[PDB]
Length: 108
Image 1 (tube, rainbow, N blue to C red):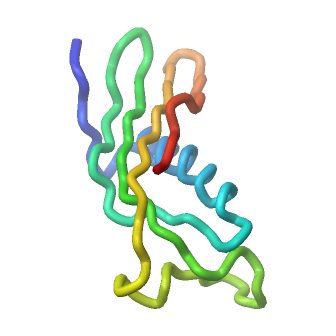
Image 2 (image 1 turned 30 degrees about the vertical axis):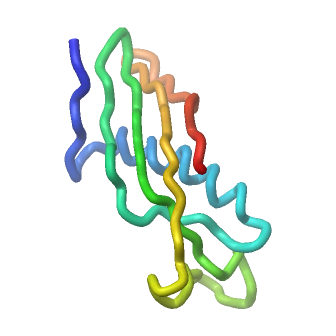
Image 3 (image 1 turned 60 degrees about the vertical axis):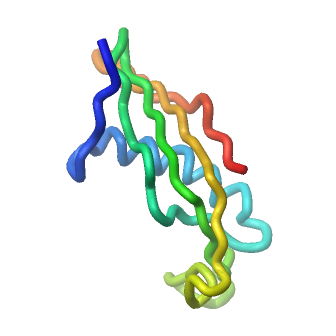
């Protein structure tokens, strides 16, 4: 057995970053929103089911949710002031039972 990396065509891995990341935005939703930036390690271990280990230097997005913006939101109008954080997402994905669940998703 071993770890298998994903490509730009794995709706499963996409549901992984969107699951944990979705939790990052709902976490900072207060001040503003947290948005991915430059992934680093997006993989899906393959055991009895799957393990989704993700890494990305999370970033932010000024606008919160409405702020009279309809649909936009953005980091800090540039990189010059949009630091980031290193977060890892751990999503177990089990086929045959469409059972996806979050696990080790922590950012810091």
